[PDB]
Image (cartoon, rainbow over all chains, first blue to last red; front, side, top):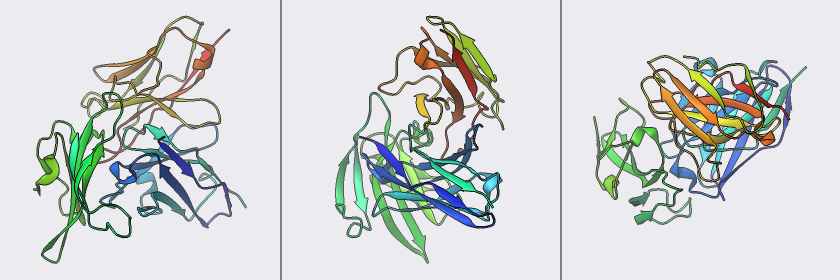
Length: 115
Length: 90
Length: 111
């Protein structure tokens, strides 16, 4: 039924950038927000931002304001997250979740940003 | 619910064009309608209409009214059937 | 505005435990939009309660939610070994509302 499946694991070098994908099936993609949350290994959940797949609008976490880019290609029901100018403490698992209640979560994408 | 459906990009997104959308939901989970449009260079372009899933913003709003100040794309959502047939903002 | 919830709590099987989530009247005091996610290690969070008190389909009735003043509380009744996980509270994210999570609580259920 409702299901978000994410892009495979990424290993990056610092300074670079990564872009993760989220493929919504099981419901009407444009019927609610997509949210992005990351998790530093052995640590809390951190909210990054919300995208409204209809309006195309975005709100961002001030922490990430101006180096994360959120987008969606509605013709394939996929939302994207792009984190640029990486570092070490960017190494996390990255989640997308459906709607503002986060009622369904993706399986996560591990991005390891190491020199 | 049922909502008004519109897709301005109906051909590329391989959806219907105009009509009604019957909302699929979960057990006693709220359902809403939304309207979304542009205002490019003094012309109002319709973007989409249809069902919106349980959203704290749309709670107990009868009129679909956008609230953001001067956004690129306008968005509103509302509660109650067909409520999204008419939309404003201020 | 961070949400604070205790680092960990332990319970015995069959017991009830309650995890709390405290913020300011700006947020938790103002809106019925607190939610509770359970997260078993190395897996994605699952939504247990939303809207302070509402429960999704397929979620055991043992999970309930409430709010008094500036703290929302998740309550797990009749503890089971499988209830052992991390529990985060968050708020609604999208529209006029911006996201936030608690530190999480590690619930340990000792058999």
